[PDB]
Image (tube, coloured by chain):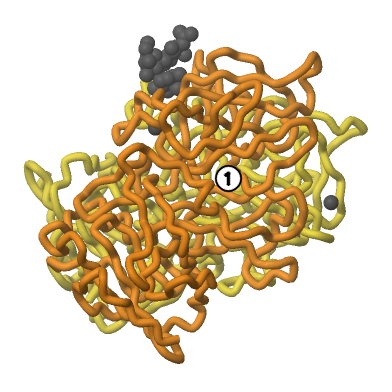
Chain colours: A orange, B yellow
Amino acid sequence: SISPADLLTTPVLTGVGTDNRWNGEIVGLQPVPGGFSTCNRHWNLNGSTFGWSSPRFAAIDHDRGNASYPGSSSSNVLELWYASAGSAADNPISQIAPDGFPDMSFVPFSGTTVPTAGWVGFGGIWNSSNGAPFVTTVQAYELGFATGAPSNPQPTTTTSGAQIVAKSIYGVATGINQATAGLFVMASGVISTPNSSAITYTPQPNRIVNAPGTPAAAPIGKNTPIMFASVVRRTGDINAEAGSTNGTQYGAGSQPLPVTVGLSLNNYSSALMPGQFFVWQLNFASGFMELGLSVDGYFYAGTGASATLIDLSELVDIRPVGPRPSTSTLVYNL
Amino acid sequence: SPADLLTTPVLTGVGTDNRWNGEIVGLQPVPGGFSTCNRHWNLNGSTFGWSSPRFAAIDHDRGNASYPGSSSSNVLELWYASAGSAADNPISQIAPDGFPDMSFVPFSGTTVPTAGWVGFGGIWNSSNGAPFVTTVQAYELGFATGAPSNPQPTTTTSGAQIVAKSIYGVATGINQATAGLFVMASGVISTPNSSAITYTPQPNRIVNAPGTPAAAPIGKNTPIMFASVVRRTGDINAEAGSTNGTQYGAGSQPLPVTVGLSLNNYSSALMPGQFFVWQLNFASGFMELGLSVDGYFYAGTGASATLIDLSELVDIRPVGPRPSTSTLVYNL
Ligand SMILES: CC(=O)N[C@@H]1[C@@H](O)[C@H](O[C@@H]2O[C@H](CO)[C@H](O)[C@H](O)[C@H]2O[C@@H]2O[C@@H](C)[C@@H](O)[C@@H](O)[C@@H]2O)[C@@H](CO)O[C@@H]1O
Ligand SMILES: [Cl-]
Ligand SMILES: [Cl-]
Ligand SMILES: [Cl-]
């Protein structure tokens, strides 16, 4: 009750807990031997986030971007919306981007190409004059951070000097050209794919967008940072779920959302010292492993150089162990 | 004990409602009573509904997809199947996990229906799982009878159909006798103009499965719903305090409560006829909320239908089991 123990209970990793990027049911642990950073909808143990999102999945809303489509015919066109990072004046957490905007770099596309590994959400453009949707622009949109929009958007992984971009991955019924227009997109995303095949866990570390000051997660001895893997829909085979014959698609997040929520409500600085992990034991049908939580809010496992996904289907229960030195190897007994 | 099911964050900004997944900001008394089963659990670990305590996606692989006329551009796309056909759903075959428990509001021409549950998604190819990309739109979903020619609302799942109809024109309509539906499970409310409407759904719009217990007043204790601010199609930018009005959606339970009831059995916590009671401490007074064995919440507000604002709620404390015949304290 004064310790971090209650942040991670059995249900968080055995079917109830979802990840803090995709809001998908967590079903695996993904080690990241090469390290990574994440700030959006990520909290530390001192009540702080470096991102721009609250620990929830609602809607993405920005009232002042540029909306356009190419060419002289407005039917069945790709709709583009973009604004500058730092323009989210109505966001009380951070003005970097609208609450819920995904922390992934923009994958550009044009013509008839559907992008690969884009964060995609449903919604459209809306009318800055009155708040009404431009009903002919509803579609699935890729959202991400870029530089060089509108003519040549390219991915960027820093928010400084960035643009926030939304582009319909399929043709909207009728395009809209308005220099000032709003964006509205539901905050629960899917992964864009051009065919039926699953791709690697998404986002890969080098696709994650981070704000200045975001601490990095790197290996500490044999302890390696992890992401939490969930089953996420993909556009090329939207019906595919866990156990699909077309392959399983994973999305990854830096924290279980229940942990993020708990961290956002509390301050755990008096409970865990810098350089300590809080450790839990994960008990499987056969064997167990330890997970450690750092003061920066990253989770670790004692898996060393391994990049192999750990399946949680046989996870039985979680028990708190207590604070440990981060230099002490987390047990891996699977 | 049930005590930990309702803690302060559940009603002070973190907890969302179990129909719209909106942040709970008010308590809405229902003096006439109501029923709800979908994504609603009792204290005996069971639901009469067809949805798990989460908001993911609505997916059904075997419906009929159509649009009217010889021109496919900018048309209203219709999808329907029979209730009882959700074979892939381990909770209930009544409907796909996440399908909304609201009766269908018919519409035509260019008029947007009032008080419809609306979600984003489209039709997909039952043969390979690929989306019909030209059918993506905002769709009204609900239970009806008489589709495809004349869908009309029904509030019982028995003999019902599940219907999705785009409220705006799709880029290119699709006619397929067997086709899938895919719609994200977090909804918005349809309105025909910028004005907010009454809290949605009203009790007479809620669809229930046979056997669902009703929540009725017990003396001066009245069943409540949990109110959240929900987006509306007529003014999608509107949030709390909009000069075009504030739109509320309502649910029978806070989702965190639903989740907890789904994981454990609370049968031993309440003797017959009892509420589990919490005290809600506001800045200038307090009130009690009671939870019945059927999973419905009550307040001692009698005939009042006035929304209770939670902006001034400070903390929640568990009280314990109390007889339901005792008026719940209301001192605000
Ligand atoms: C062309 C015209 O007159 N449009 C107005 C529109 O400007 C109004 O918007 C509100 O304007 C005030 C300033 O006068 C504030 O900026 C409000 O925040 C703004 O409302 C918000 O945005 C609008 C677009 C709606 O989405 C509303 O629900 C939001 O609260 C509106 C509202 O008075 O009226 C006319 O459309
Ligand atoms: Cl925002
Ligand atoms: Cl039918
Ligand atoms: Cl196809």
Determine if the C-beta at disc 1 is less than 8 A from ligand 2.
Answer: no
Position in image of residue A49 (x %, y %) = 29, 45
Say left or right for A261 vs B287.
Answer: right
The residue located at (39%, 61%) in the rendering is A256
| A71 w.r.t. A255: above or below | above
Residue B155 visible in this rendered orientation of the protein = yes
- Helix or strand or loop: what does disc 1 sit on? strand
Q: How crowded is mark 1: few (under 14 residues within 10 Å), some or many (20 or more)?
A: many
Query: Which amino acid type is shown beneath numbered disc 1?
Result: Trp
Residue A80 in percent (x, y) is at 64, 26
Quarter of the image holding residue B107?
A: top right
Q: Is residue A316 left or right of residue B26?
A: right
Judging depth in this view, the residue of A181 and A246 nearest the camera is: A246
Residue occupying image coordinates x 74% and y 61%: B61
Judge by depth and name the residue closer to the eye, B299 or A14.
Answer: A14
Residue B91 placed where, x, y %?
Answer: 56, 72
Query: Which residue is more in the foreground, B150 or A271?
Result: A271
Seen in the picture, residue A187 relative to B327 is either above or below; the reply is: above
Q: Position of residue B213 (x, y in %)?
A: 43, 68
Q: Which residue is drawn at 80% across and 14% down?
A: A72
Left or right relative to A273: residue B18: right
Q: Can residue B216 be seen in this view?
A: no
Quadrant of residue B249 within the rendered picture: top left
In the image, farthest residue toward the right: B70
* Residue that badge 1 annotates: A119
